[PDB]
Length: 100
Length: 75
Length: 75
Length: 94
Image (cartoon, rainbow over all chains, first blue to last red; front, top):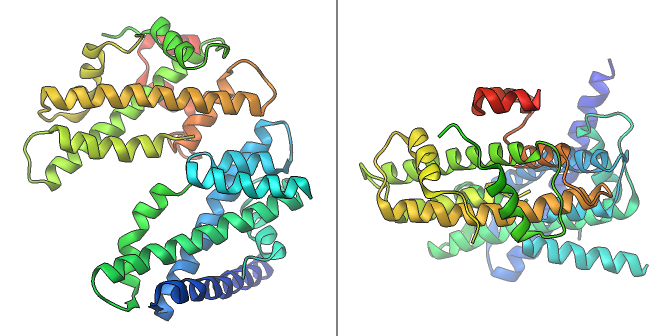
């Protein structure tokens, strides 16, 4: 029920993430003087798609822990703690949002 | 460029185990940044691995080689 | 042997976070997480020693394992 | 100053590993354990403050073991407790 539509949604998202992965990868190729094979790009796209699942489940856990059903910048900050570099980066970004 | 809000939102809702779970706009932008960093990191690491082997071309093998460390080092 | 260092666990966390109060039996859960950390650490060091063709676990295997497992252990 | 006794760390580690471990290796395990506690202190703080509390509750520790990937949909906390905590202490949690 809604299963076929969900499969279409999944293909839509895979392809969207893949496009964006291509664009970002191209910036990197330019920076470093390399060429990424199609298969490499696709691989990174699929890895990224998959990691999204854990991000989403952890964000949801973090919001629930706060008796809160909507995810905020505090949950994303928590999500980024385990990598100090990442935490600094994303916290910078988040403050930048705060200023508006 | 970067990940679009719509894409990130749908991507996240897809995996929520609670129907009422939502993500506000700031979190969506933040997550877009986080995902972008993830991708740039995967690409930069695979690139580095290929360069240390004196290759211009990054192949799926280079990605596979760098992935576990990446996932470990990432969140 | 079968005993839990409840007071020690509390004191360790208190030395790290003085104004941080624990509750209930939470020390017992902390202890659990610690046991399991030790278990993962052992598995990883042993894997390392085997990959190193070593019958014995040595400081180098344990150091590499610690880096990995302490990473996996972050919240 | 405060730390888990060396003997206990050795008992657990060796009980699990079933493989010879050098003395110096154990010194590494001890330092790793110190670091483990430093980190979870940080974490439990962040978790409890996240929920608006000044105290660390059970939910905080279970959240930690979830983030550590010990507690999962297929491996509930109560199963880990039943498995790894000696008979007496598990009664306190159930």
